[PDB]
Image (cartoon, coloured by chain):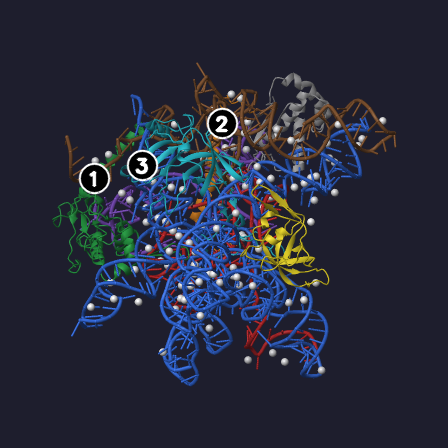
Chain colours: B cyan, C green, D orange, E yellow, F brown, G blue, H red, I purple
Amino acid sequence: MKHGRKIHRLSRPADQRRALLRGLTTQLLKHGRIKTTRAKASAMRKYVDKMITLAKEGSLHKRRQALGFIYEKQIVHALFAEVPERYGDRNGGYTRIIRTLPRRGDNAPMAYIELV
Amino acid sequence: SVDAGIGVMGTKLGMMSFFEEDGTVVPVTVIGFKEGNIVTQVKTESTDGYNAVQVGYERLRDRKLTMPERGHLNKAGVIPMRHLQEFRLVSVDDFTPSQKLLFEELFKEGDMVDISGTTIGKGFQGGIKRHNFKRGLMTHGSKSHRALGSIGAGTTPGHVYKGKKMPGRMGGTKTKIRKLKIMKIDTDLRVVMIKGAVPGKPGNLLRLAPAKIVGKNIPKN
Amino acid sequence: RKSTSASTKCTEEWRQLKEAVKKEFAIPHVPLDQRWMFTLEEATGPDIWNTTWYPKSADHVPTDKKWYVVDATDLILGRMASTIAIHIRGKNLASYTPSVDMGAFVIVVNADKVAVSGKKRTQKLYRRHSGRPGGLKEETFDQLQKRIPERIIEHAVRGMLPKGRLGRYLFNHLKVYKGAEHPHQAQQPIDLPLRDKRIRVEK
Amino acid sequence: AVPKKRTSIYKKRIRKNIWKKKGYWAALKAFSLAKSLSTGNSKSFFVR
Amino acid sequence: MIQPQTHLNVADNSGARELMCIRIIGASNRRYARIGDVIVAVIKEAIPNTPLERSEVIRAVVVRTCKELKRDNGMIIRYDDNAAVIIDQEGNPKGTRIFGAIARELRQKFAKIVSLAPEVL
RNA sequence: AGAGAAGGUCACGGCGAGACGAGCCGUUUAUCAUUACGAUAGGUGUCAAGUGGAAGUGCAGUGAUGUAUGCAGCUGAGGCAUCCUAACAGACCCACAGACUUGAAC
RNA sequence: UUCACAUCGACGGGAAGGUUUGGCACCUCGAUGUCGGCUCUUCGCCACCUGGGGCUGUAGUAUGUUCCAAGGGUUGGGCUGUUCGCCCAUUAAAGCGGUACGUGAGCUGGGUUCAGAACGUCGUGAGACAGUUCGGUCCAUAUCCGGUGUGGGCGUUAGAGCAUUGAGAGGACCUUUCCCUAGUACGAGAGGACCGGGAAGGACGCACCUCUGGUGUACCAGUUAUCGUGCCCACGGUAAACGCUGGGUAGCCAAGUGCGGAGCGGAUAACUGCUGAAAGCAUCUAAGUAGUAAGCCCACCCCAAGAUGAGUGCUCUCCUA
RNA sequence: UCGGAGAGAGGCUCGGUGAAAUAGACAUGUCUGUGAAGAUGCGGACUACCUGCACCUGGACAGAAAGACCCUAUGAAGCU
RNA sequence: AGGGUGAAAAGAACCCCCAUCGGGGAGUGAAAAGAACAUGAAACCGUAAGCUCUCAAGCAGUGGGAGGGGGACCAGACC
Ligand SMILES: [Mg+2]
Ligand SMILES: [Mg+2]
Ligand SMILES: [Mg+2]
Ligand SMILES: [Mg+2]
Ligand SMILES: [Mg+2]
Ligand SMILES: [Mg+2]
Ligand SMILES: [Mg+2]
Ligand SMILES: [Mg+2]
Ligand SMILES: [Mg+2]
Ligand SMILES: [Mg+2]
Ligand SMILES: [Mg+2]
Ligand SMILES: [Mg+2]
Ligand SMILES: [Mg+2]
Ligand SMILES: [Mg+2]
Ligand SMILES: [Mg+2]
Ligand SMILES: [Mg+2]
Ligand SMILES: [Mg+2]
Ligand SMILES: [Mg+2]
Ligand SMILES: [Mg+2]
Ligand SMILES: [Mg+2]
Ligand SMILES: [Mg+2]
Ligand SMILES: [Mg+2]
Ligand SMILES: [Mg+2]
Ligand SMILES: [Mg+2]
Ligand SMILES: [Mg+2]
Ligand SMILES: [Mg+2]
Ligand SMILES: [Mg+2]
Ligand SMILES: [Mg+2]
Ligand SMILES: [Mg+2]
Ligand SMILES: [Mg+2]
Ligand SMILES: [Mg+2]
Ligand SMILES: [Mg+2]
Ligand SMILES: [Mg+2]
Ligand SMILES: [Mg+2]
Ligand SMILES: [Mg+2]
Ligand SMILES: [Mg+2]
Ligand SMILES: [Mg+2]
Ligand SMILES: [Mg+2]
Ligand SMILES: [Mg+2]
Ligand SMILES: [Mg+2]
Ligand SMILES: [Mg+2]
Ligand SMILES: [Mg+2]
Ligand SMILES: [Mg+2]
Ligand SMILES: [Mg+2]
Ligand SMILES: [Mg+2]
Ligand SMILES: [Mg+2]
Ligand SMILES: [Mg+2]
Ligand SMILES: [Mg+2]
Ligand SMILES: [Mg+2]
Ligand SMILES: [Mg+2]
Ligand SMILES: [Mg+2]
Ligand SMILES: [Mg+2]
Ligand SMILES: [Mg+2]
Ligand SMILES: [Mg+2]
Ligand SMILES: [Mg+2]
Ligand SMILES: [Mg+2]
Ligand SMILES: [Mg+2]
Ligand SMILES: [Mg+2]
Ligand SMILES: [Mg+2]
Ligand SMILES: [Mg+2]
Ligand SMILES: [Mg+2]
Ligand SMILES: [Mg+2]
Ligand SMILES: [Mg+2]
Ligand SMILES: [Mg+2]
Ligand SMILES: [Mg+2]
Ligand SMILES: [Mg+2]
Ligand SMILES: [Mg+2]
Ligand SMILES: [Mg+2]
Ligand SMILES: [Mg+2]
Ligand SMILES: [Mg+2]
Ligand SMILES: [Mg+2]
Ligand SMILES: [Mg+2]
Ligand SMILES: [Mg+2]
Ligand SMILES: [Mg+2]
Ligand SMILES: [Mg+2]
Ligand SMILES: [Mg+2]
Ligand SMILES: [Mg+2]
Ligand SMILES: [Mg+2]
Ligand SMILES: [Mg+2]
Ligand SMILES: [Mg+2]
Ligand SMILES: [Mg+2]
Ligand SMILES: [Mg+2]
Ligand SMILES: [Mg+2]
Ligand SMILES: [Mg+2]
Ligand SMILES: [Mg+2]
Ligand SMILES: [Mg+2]
Ligand SMILES: [Mg+2]
Ligand SMILES: [Mg+2]
Ligand SMILES: [Mg+2]
Ligand SMILES: [Mg+2]
Ligand SMILES: [Mg+2]
Ligand SMILES: [Mg+2]
Ligand SMILES: [Mg+2]
Ligand SMILES: [Mg+2]
Ligand SMILES: [Mg+2]
Ligand SMILES: [Mg+2]
Ligand SMILES: [Mg+2]
Ligand SMILES: [Mg+2]
Ligand SMILES: [Mg+2]
Ligand SMILES: [Mg+2]
Ligand SMILES: [Mg+2]
Ligand SMILES: [Mg+2]
Ligand SMILES: [Mg+2]
Ligand SMILES: [Mg+2]
Ligand SMILES: [Mg+2]
């Protein structure tokens, strides 16, 4: 069993799950809100926040860390620009998760993850 | 199962190592406590058919309790409590509802205890893990490996036996551990250190009694 | 919640009407005590004289039954259990029917003082089986009588009752106590008649 | 392993009723959910 | 963790270069030789022109394991090889001078052997 | 028939519980001022712990590379804090003083 | 040595069993199939060891034989298709049988020597062989019963929440060396005790992660090839489901750590007994009673009122018109 | 020895689509006895609330048709 | 392998649900017989009403028939 194995598997192997999560975050930081499956969202919380907390410090070191996570440079630079302004006072908790009607095709429970 | 002596309940906090002056390292479980170990109810042979004492343990917010239970603890005049339990004695004259227990009074050093607890649930388990079945050959031609084996004899009897051991759910049960020892008591932190392992992971709920010894603490039959 | 809405009201009312009309025209029940051949009413009814009588539900109603008490002290196990079985089953009433319970209740008291001939106290063997292999358990009669002595008489009468639905339902009418006392004094138990000669042992 | 016999009409009717009882619990969740979205007060939920 | 078919280095003069353990004694049905158990070995390789011929059944005590011995100090010892010393049924070593380290765990049953040691642990 | 008893189920946040059901814990997150009982998960802050000395910029060197800044940097499935996010909105089941007889009491 | 009956027991007889080799042909022929291992049971007792005894040609230690006793145990290898058996090293001892070779819709070798080939032998020959030799396909999604777990419904006579009694059911009550007793009884010596105490081990069971570790595709570090991020720097991808290596927390785990097997409780088997008649003697038995077994039953440990015989206890709730 | 952990594809739950071999009727317990001589179905006792699900494969002389082995047929064919 | 709407296509204008199919009215028709259309058995799939099963062992019936229900005219009967 798993006792205290905490990770989100998303029913994919390691490589894929990494790449998926990176992708989903460059999406959220590009569009600011997105529609996904409940599991994917819940899993994606952690990495969203890693990125934001990353940008709050702003060091060249941190910026290279984020660059090597998110896929698209432009979104990274914009992150380091906006974040001190928008999130400066917020200690943690940068994402809202709002669930919806499930999907038609498979009846997979959906969700809306918002950059809050 | 008449029990020798009043027991108390406690909470497993996890294990550490503990030295003795001569450099003997003893692994010990540290058993914490919480506000509680209050005698709730007392049962007389006349009234209930037998002699027992119900001690409550973990305190609690009043909302979370149910009306029947809250009304059980206002008859006692005690604070709201999560877990109730019973100890079965051969003599109850010493106990009044609302009376409180201290584990420093009941347990000295070098005394023998018995720790009852609930075990780690390992879920649904195979024949190997659950009963220690030897596994069959891994290689030369063999298609079995971790499988159960044959489960019974041939045409006669022609049905499997009762209780013939099979894969099912393992762990997660009341388990006694007999004759442990008490290494040190800390009055400061109100904690009891015990030599050895006690069931279940930290945050558990334990029941400790003075150890039943089938010759000398108990009714002969 | 019992609705007092006009609907349910109406329904119960009507049902009591149906019940009224069905009670008026139906043939009255005449219990069997000095009951003469026929009432001028039955004489309009179906033929119960040239057909075999069968009991109706008014008869066997549980509330009416005789109660009995057997002092089991110095009685002989089997010989008593036969008599008990007869009375429970109903075989001593003229009204007996195999398919119905016309029987009594029987209360057996002093169930540790019951007497048994021969070396039987140390020999007769009560076995019961788990249902696993090597699941056999054996008691001598005496271990049993020291441990839970009522089981002895319960187990000796159950053998002589019918088996099957009416059998089991019957067996619930056998009320056994180890002490000299029973809490049934409300039921007004009569004592049980014993016509057997050898049933009473003397030392 | 095969079915030595064929399954009796009534027993099959019970097994299939069991499988139809799940529709009943899903109908309760569905009802509760509509009554939620029908007050427009939920900020956890969203519909378009 | 010496068990049957295990090969062992000999720690003394007695004229065997290598042993192969075939049994464990006094342990009833345990399968593990740990330090200070008597094992029945046979000689595989020997030192030429010595009282000991290869293919001999002999007794030896196990002085070194690659498994780890735990004393009560919480102290632990792990050697790099397996080794045993060839003895009599009296507890006296056949060979008269021993190599390598040993432990105070052997002092109880074997005096001789701890005596002849270049080092004690 | 209106209403929703005690309680239960569901919903919602979860787990050292779990194949699914089940189990257990939570669901506005207290107040305090002298105990404890009102932080479930995530995030954030700090700590145990792991790894083993970040990037950048300096110096040394023809150079690969070394050395200082620095128990660094990353990680932190574990503890402790802090309501920043989500425990919103809610729904369903459920309430003939307990048929009939007999004694005892009053 | 004397002595039939310590131990053997010739010549003969009387039996039980249904495990060997057989007779029968009642059985199934369509696809109801033999011997060994693996895994997994289970039962018998004609007892190999462990518990208690009687007799001895029993001094002691160790036997021999027999009685009650089946609770528990009964190793690892070299060798064989094998039942059989032989040996090596141990060991308390390395029991014999039944269950369709116990077990092939659980696994696997041979065997029904299937088709290829070769040897010996028989046959002019095609081919043959209770000769040998090399090679040689058995499938399976569990309907029902049976089982191991785990739920719902309903019952439990108003409805609930807790806490429990224990009918019944199971798990486990195992065993070896060593040390005191005492080099004491015993014996001329050599040898060397019963009984009762104490430690260490084995196997098995129940838990556990403090240590020692294994894994740990949560993580950290090196590093090759190569393509990305404009280029150096620095990171990213790929080398299936880690590119390859070096570490690892939490978890799970054992080889690691703890703990367990207690009973001047009850009743018996064999046996040893006390009072003591039927037979004024005797007699362990007919009256009555005493010791006594790893056995039997309670006690120990989990489960357990669907225990429909549905238990007891505390508390809570039954509004409005 | 003596197993341990991990990764994938299934297994498991939810939504979509959706077979098969099999099948006298099946309201389909255990022991023991009987019996065409190995019974859920006959007898006697014993045990069993109703019904799912996941697992397991001892039974149903389980399933996939002529038994390859043996014999029969005044059958068939190949070969000598 | 696939036959039988009606005598006549008079094969259903118009409104409603309405993306089509499909449907409900209206209208045609002796009849809707409504195009997958004539009589339309059984297996098999259901829906409604009467009685009844959750301590039970059984080739499922039969003889006895408790209790409950239904259409009667020979109401003492039948189901
Ligand atoms: Mg890869
Ligand atoms: Mg890939
Ligand atoms: Mg983090
Ligand atoms: Mg678990
Ligand atoms: Mg094995
Ligand atoms: Mg394989
Ligand atoms: Mg040789
Ligand atoms: Mg020197
Ligand atoms: Mg309510
Ligand atoms: Mg939940
Ligand atoms: Mg629930
Ligand atoms: Mg709420
Ligand atoms: Mg938190
Ligand atoms: Mg937490
Ligand atoms: Mg640097
Ligand atoms: Mg790096
Ligand atoms: Mg330079
Ligand atoms: Mg550190
Ligand atoms: Mg706060
Ligand atoms: Mg909020
Ligand atoms: Mg009343
Ligand atoms: Mg009344
Ligand atoms: Mg003789
Ligand atoms: Mg024949
Ligand atoms: Mg077949
Ligand atoms: Mg015998
Ligand atoms: Mg003996
Ligand atoms: Mg003897
Ligand atoms: Mg002698
Ligand atoms: Mg035995
Ligand atoms: Mg046995
Ligand atoms: Mg045995
Ligand atoms: Mg062997
Ligand atoms: Mg020996
Ligand atoms: Mg011995
Ligand atoms: Mg056997
Ligand atoms: Mg075999
Ligand atoms: Mg089979
Ligand atoms: Mg072959
Ligand atoms: Mg020739
Ligand atoms: Mg020949
Ligand atoms: Mg080949
Ligand atoms: Mg099934
Ligand atoms: Mg079943
Ligand atoms: Mg059940
Ligand atoms: Mg239930
Ligand atoms: Mg109820
Ligand atoms: Mg209920
Ligand atoms: Mg509670
Ligand atoms: Mg209990
Ligand atoms: Mg009991
Ligand atoms: Mg039962
Ligand atoms: Mg028992
Ligand atoms: Mg015992
Ligand atoms: Mg002397
Ligand atoms: Mg002794
Ligand atoms: Mg021991
Ligand atoms: Mg560890
Ligand atoms: Mg740890
Ligand atoms: Mg590693
Ligand atoms: Mg680890
Ligand atoms: Mg480029
Ligand atoms: Mg490049
Ligand atoms: Mg890389
Ligand atoms: Mg690429
Ligand atoms: Mg490729
Ligand atoms: Mg690979
Ligand atoms: Mg690695
Ligand atoms: Mg251990
Ligand atoms: Mg005794
Ligand atoms: Mg006696
Ligand atoms: Mg005598
Ligand atoms: Mg005399
Ligand atoms: Mg005498
Ligand atoms: Mg006598
Ligand atoms: Mg005993
Ligand atoms: Mg003992
Ligand atoms: Mg109850
Ligand atoms: Mg009743
Ligand atoms: Mg009662
Ligand atoms: Mg595994
Ligand atoms: Mg896996
Ligand atoms: Mg696939
Ligand atoms: Mg599906
Ligand atoms: Mg078909
Ligand atoms: Mg049935
Ligand atoms: Mg016969
Ligand atoms: Mg039979
Ligand atoms: Mg039968
Ligand atoms: Mg029948
Ligand atoms: Mg089967
Ligand atoms: Mg299988
Ligand atoms: Mg059968
Ligand atoms: Mg049949
Ligand atoms: Mg002929
Ligand atoms: Mg011919
Ligand atoms: Mg139309
Ligand atoms: Mg369209
Ligand atoms: Mg249309
Ligand atoms: Mg019309
Ligand atoms: Mg018209
Ligand atoms: Mg038609
Ligand atoms: Mg019953
Ligand atoms: Mg009933
Ligand atoms: Mg029935």
Identify the chain of the residue marked 2, using the numbered disc in the image: D
Instruction: Identify residue for label 2.
Output: D34
Q: For this rendering, which residue is in front, G243 or B109?
A: B109
- Percent from the top left, x then y, of residue B73? 35, 28
| Residue E18 seen from this side | yes
Under tag 1, what secondary structure?
helix
Q: Is residue B197 left or right of residue C178?
A: right
| Residue B174 seen from this side | no
Circles 3 and 2: CB atoms closer than 8 Å: no
Q: Is residue G257 left or right of residue B101?
A: right
- Picture quarter with ligand 11: top left
- Asked if both marks, 3 and 2, belong to the same chain, the answer given is no
Establish whether ligand 22 lies closer than 8 Å to the Cβ of label 1: no
Q: Is residue B63 left or right of residue C26?
A: right
Q: CA distance from mark 3 to mark 2?
A: 58 Å
Instruction: Identify residue for label 1.
Output: C23
Instruction: Identify residue for label 3.
Output: B92
Question: Label 1 amino acid?
Answer: Lys
Which quarter shows the C terminus of chain C? bottom left
Identify the chain of the residue marked 1, using the numbered disc in the image: C
Q: CA distance from mark 3 to mark 1?
A: 62 Å
Q: Is residue I36 left or right of residue H39?
A: right
- Percent from the top left, x then y, of residue G81? 60, 67
For the point 28% across and 50% down, the residue is: C148
Under tag 2, what secondary structure?
helix
User: Which mark's residue is nearer the viewer, 3 or 2?
Assistant: 3
Q: Is residue E31 above or below residue C1?
A: below
Q: For this rendering, which residue is in front, B83 or G98?
A: B83
Establish whether ligand 12 lies closer than 8 Å to the Cβ of label 2: no
